[PDB]
Image (cartoon, grey):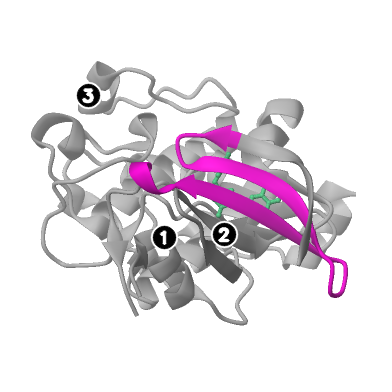
Amino acid sequence: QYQVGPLLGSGGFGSVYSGIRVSDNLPVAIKHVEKDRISDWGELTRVPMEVVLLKKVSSGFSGVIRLLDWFERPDSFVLILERPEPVQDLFDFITERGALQEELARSFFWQVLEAVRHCHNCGVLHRDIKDENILIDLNRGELKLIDFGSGALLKDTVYTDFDGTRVYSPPEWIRYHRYHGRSAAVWSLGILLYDMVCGDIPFEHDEEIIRGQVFFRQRVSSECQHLIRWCLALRPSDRPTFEEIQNHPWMQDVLLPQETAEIHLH
Ligand SMILES: O=C1N/C(=N/c2ccccc2Cl)S/C1=C\c1ccc(O)c([N+](=O)[O-])c1
């Protein structure tokens, strides 16, 4: 069914390879996850939650990665995922190009917000929003959310489990090992937006996160700084909602994805 290509990445959430669907030469990604590292299971048969979550967000909307198929092996699960070509993740993009212009960051952040709003609307919490988990369709200027391997079903009660990225985690998790989905998601969005406009994350140590003092190492507008400091409110209830973020003055007059490519990506 699939012609396997080179390894696109390896880590805690498995190994991911480049692939070709022999049927129509469709570009795909082949993700392998060891069953022994899957703590969360669900159904709709017994599959990892990642498969469950991915099928809930599966749609015609292109802000979230698409699950094409999956397979069960004796000791692993194999995910066949959408693969844009060419593509580059936000981490490598910022790593090679540095801090993004606010016009480009606005377009990107907007697309991320629309994707996470989609997940939440579908009952899914991603729980690992970051530059590494965002793909860029370089031709269409469209962003895609990837890696749902640390995500859970969205709920209104407290989460006592977390296995996402620590430097993107909120101060309520660091201290109390407790967080609520939406507020915690907004925090990671604040970390992400800072990362976009400054070229790196604001906090590296637990002590910095608890304190939540944001220092700008780059020239950033007052409105962007405001939105960032707002998302990074210590008290979760002082954090904006997704509506309040997208009605923020800095989020005004966003570029269409195709405009974003012709100006910034070509
Ligand atoms: O849903 C997903 N979870 C992922 N996790 C990983 C992320 C980094 C390294 C290894 C793994 Cl398994 S990758 C992934 C989807 C992708 C789909 C297409 C694609 O080109 C890529 N990519 O380039 O890494 C990734």
- Separation of marks 3 and 1 at Cα, in angstroms: 33 Å
- Separation of marks 1 and 2 at Cα, in angstroms: 9 Å
Question: Ligand 1 within 8 A of label 1's CB?
Answer: yes
Spot occupied by residue 264 in the image (x, y as percentages of width and height): 81, 48
Spot occupied by residue 171 in the image (x, y as percentages of width and height): 21, 34
Q: Earlier in the sequence, mark 1 or mark 2?
A: 1
**56 sits to left or right of 172:** right
Helix, strand or loop at label 2? It is strand
- Separation of marks 2 and 3 at Cα, in angstroms: 39 Å
Q: Residue furthest front?
A: 74
Q: Residue at x 72, y 68 (%)?
A: 256
Quadrant in which residue 144 is drawn: bottom right
Q: Which residues are magenta?
A: 10-37
Circle 2 residue? 79
- Disc 2 residue type (three-letter): Leu
Answer whether labels 1 and 2 touch (C-beta < 8 Å): yes
Helix, strand or loop at label 3? It is helix
**For mark 2, does the 10 Å Cα neighbourhood hold few (<14), some (14 to 19), or many (20 or more) residues?**
many
Q: Is residue 261 above or below residue 199?
A: below
Q: Residue at x 74, y 65 (%)?
A: 257
Question: Ligand 1 within 8 A of label 2's CB?
Answer: yes
Q: Residue at x 30, y 25 (%)?
A: 213
**266 sits to left or right of 264:** right
- Disc 1 residue type (three-letter): Glu
Circle 3 residue? 211
**6 sits to left or right of 223:** right
Circle 1 residue? 50
